[PDB]
Image (cartoon, coloured by chain):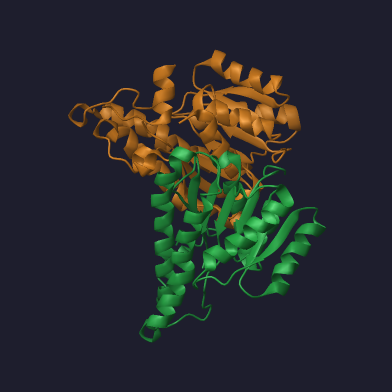
Chain colours: A green, B orange
Amino acid sequence: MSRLTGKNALVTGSSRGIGRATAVRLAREGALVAVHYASNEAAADETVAQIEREGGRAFPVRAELGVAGDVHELFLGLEQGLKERTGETTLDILVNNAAVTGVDGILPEDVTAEQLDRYYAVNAKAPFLLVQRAVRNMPDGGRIINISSGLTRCAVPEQVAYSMTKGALEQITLHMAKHLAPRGITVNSVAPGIRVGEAGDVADVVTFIATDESRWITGAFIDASGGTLLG
Amino acid sequence: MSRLTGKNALVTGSSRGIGRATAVRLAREGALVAVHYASNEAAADETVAQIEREGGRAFPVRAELGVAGDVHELFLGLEQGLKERTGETTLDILVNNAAVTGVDGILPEDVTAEQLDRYYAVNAKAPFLLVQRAVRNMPDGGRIINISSGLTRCAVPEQVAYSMTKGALEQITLHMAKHLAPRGITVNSVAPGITGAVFDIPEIVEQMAGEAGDVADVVTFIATDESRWITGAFIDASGGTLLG
C-alpha cells in the first residue's frame, strides 16, 4: 500500500483514462505525481483534486507534445514543481502514456502524410526524447514504463497509423532496457486491450512495474489486455 | 503488505530455490502455503520453519511427481492440511514450480527416450493434471502460475529435452487462460533467466545445491488481485538475460 514513498513520477497524458488511473495509483503508493496535460486543464485539475482527496500529492504540468520545445517546456514545469515540493529535481518514474488517437480510426487509403507526422511526433519521437531527458534526473533503480497497445499484435486496418507509432515505442523498450541495465533502470512496455474493465485494471499493472518488486523485469512486453490478445 | 489474507496456496517443489522463495513471499502476504516436496523432507521442513519464524502459516505435503497417482496423493495431503487449519479445501493459488532440470547439458545426439519421458512426466503432464484437479477447488479470483524458462526463447542445444517440456508448459498457460477466464481464474507463465554452458536459474539452484527472490517477487505480484488484467501471458523475469 506504500511502496513509492519519496519517489517522484511523471505520467504524460494523465488528465484522463489509463494516464489518470495510473497517476491516482502511483500517488496512493506515496509517489509525488506530475500530472502532465496538453490543454485540458480542468481534467488535469480533476486528477490532482482526486489525488489530494485520497491523501496523496500531485501537481499539474502543461506541455503541448509533438511541437518545437515540447521536452524543454515539460521539464521546465516538472523541475520547478519537484524542486518546490521536494528540494530536488530527481525523477524516479517516467510513464510514457500521452498519445494522439482516433477512436473511429482512419481507413489506410485516407491516412495523410500530416496525420503520419502528428501520430509519430507525439507517440514515438516525444517518448524517445522524454526518455533521453528523464535519465539525466533518474537515479539507479529508476523506472521507465511505455504504454503500448495490443494493436501491435492484433491487426486492425483503421488503426494502422496509431499502431505504427506503438511498434516504434516498443523498440524504445527493447533497446533502452539493454542500454540502461547497468544503471539498474528498467524499461518495459505495458499493452492494454484495444467482462467490463476499467482504466484501473491496466493502471494496477503499471503501478506494480513502478515498484521495487519488478526489478527483474526489463525490456519486456507486459500483456495487460484482460486476455483480449488470447484469441 | 497483506494482499493474500485468507488465501490458500500450493507451491510445487518449494523445498528450495524459486519455490522456497515463492512459498516464503506468499506466506508473508498472509497466504496459508502448502510446501510440496517429492523426497527432500528436511528442506521442505526448513521452508515451513522459515515461514513460521516470520509469523506466517505453512505445512509440508509430499508427492513424487511424474508417476501414476501423483495428483491424487498430493491432493489428499493438501486437502487434509487445509481442512485441519481452515475447515475448507479451497485452493486460491497454484504455482507449478516443481521440475526435472538439465543440471548437466545432454548433447542432442545422447538424449534418450527415457530422459524425454521423465522431463515430460514432471514438467508438462503433471502440471496439466494438477491444473485440472486444482480448478475443482478454486473460486473466482484464483491464480495459476506456471514457472517456465528463458530457454523457450534462447537456443541451447544441450537443453533441448528440458526446453521441449517448458514449450508444452507455456501452451497450458495460453489455452487454459482462455478456458478459465469465465471463472475469473488467470493463468500466466513466469520465465526465470539463463547464464561455455548455458543454464536457467532452476538448473543453477540444483548445481549449487538471477536470484530466486527476484523471480519469486514477480510470482507473488501475479498471485495478487492487482494482476487481474494479466492472463495467458509470458512474464519475463530473466533480469534482462533474454535481451542477450
User: Which quadrant: the N terminus of chain B?
Assistant: top right
Describe residue A116's horizontal placement relative to residue B85 as left or right: left
In this view, which residue lies farthest toward the top?
B42
Work out whether residue B148 can be spotted.
yes
Vertical comparison of A29 with A115: above or below: above
Nearer the observer, A225 or A123: A123
Work out whether residue A199 can be spotted.
no
Describe residue A197's horizontal placement relative to residue A165 as left or right: right
Where is residue A74 shown, x and y percent of the image?
Answer: 59, 64
Vertical comparison of B56 with A224: above or below: above
Vertical comparison of B192 with B16: above or below: below
Q: Determine which quarter of the picture holds residue B191.
A: top left
Q: Residue at x 42, y 29 (%)?
A: B201
Q: Residue at x 43, y 47 (%)?
A: A177
Where is residue A70 shown, x and y percent of the image?
Answer: 53, 68
Q: Residue at x 61, y 44 (%)?
A: A211
